[PDB]
Image: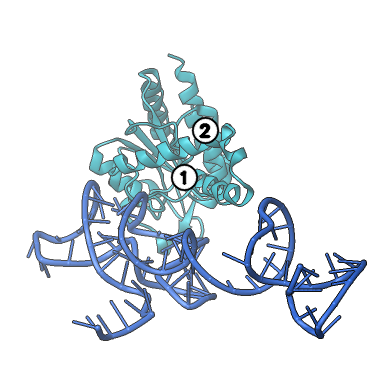
Chain colours: A cyan, B blue
Amino acid sequence: YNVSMRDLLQAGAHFGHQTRFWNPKMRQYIFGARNKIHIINLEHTVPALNDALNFANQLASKKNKVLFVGTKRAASNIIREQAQRAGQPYVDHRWLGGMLTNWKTLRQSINRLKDLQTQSQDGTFAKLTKREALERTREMEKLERSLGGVKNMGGLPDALFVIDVDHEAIAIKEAKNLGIPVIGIVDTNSNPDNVDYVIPGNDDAIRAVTLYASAMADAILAGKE
RNA sequence: GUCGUCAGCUCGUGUCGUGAGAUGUUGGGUUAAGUCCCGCAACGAGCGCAACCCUUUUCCUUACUUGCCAGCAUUUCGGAU
């Protein structure tokens, strides 16, 4: 499930943000600047990505659960589809404040969503009249877009795989608080201090995020033990 | 009694701060209303608002006296009979 380097180049992982938006903590990876934007070399990307894939594969072999976090508009559909393929918990919409550090309260949310979903599955919704049907149905819609991804999830995850560390800094902080390891895609304008497995690469390209999520999901499925 | 029928007043877990505290309850529309809908380190609850109670406006069913009189008949022309 390794990515080689040519696939990374075709995806476009080598691009970064403009030089004036950089974070000086990525000097080791930034390599050079072809234009007014930085170019992240894939020579450091490939091995770190391979270690991340190996770690996730070992976690899947041990049967641990790896949560997926991407909330950008570009990466939302990709994380949704790939996490559905991999059968692991996912967070598509905005990170709720206290999803992990305040899991006890989110549990009740999962429970009443399941309850009202079973109500819709059975005939209680049918005997509920039309206007009651309608506000309970948008109750469905909002709660499902809010926490549908973590509905199967019943405990704290063993790893957190994140698309944009800056865009999802809150999740990284909660993971640091609870001690759970983080694998994340960091870019030139990003802070890598609280990421245990730091893979450097592009984050805006839909090809790049698709490649990353494909590698992650294929490793998780390839656990097979 | 009064502010005043004013729309406000609080609580638990989680975060930020050495701390008193803060957040949530703020931000944009809307409403008679913290009324409702969107966003957001917050996620969840109660008392308040509204409704449930009484009365009035249209119709139906049951009930036909001590109340009623459209049709019939008799009338001292008084539903008087």
Q: Does residue B24 sit above or below B43 in this rendering?
A: below
* Residue A168 screen position, x and y as percent: 39, 50
Nearer to me, A35 or A172: A172
Q: Does residue A65 sit above or below A191 in this rendering?
A: above
Q: Which residue is mark 2?
A: A118
Q: Is residue B64 left or right of residue A49?
A: right
Nearer to me, A20 or A179: A179
Q: Earlier in the sequence, mark 2 or mark 1?
A: 1
Chain containing mark 1: A
Determine the residue positioned at 53% across, 35% down. A119
Q: Amino acid at mark 1?
A: Gly
Q: Amino acid at mark 2?
A: Thr
Nearer to me, A214 or A4: A214
* Mark linked to residue A38: none
Q: Which residue is mark 1?
A: A70
Q: Is residue B15 left or right of residue B55?
A: left
Q: CA distance from mark 2 to mark 1?
A: 28 Å
Q: How many marks?
A: 2
Q: Is residue A50 left or right of residue A15?
A: left
* Residue A173 screen position, x and y as percent: 29, 48
Secondary element under disc 2, as helix, strand or loop, is helix
Q: Are marks 2 and 1 in contact (CB under 8 Å)?
A: no
> Are the numbered discs 2 and 1 placed on the same chain, yes or no?
yes
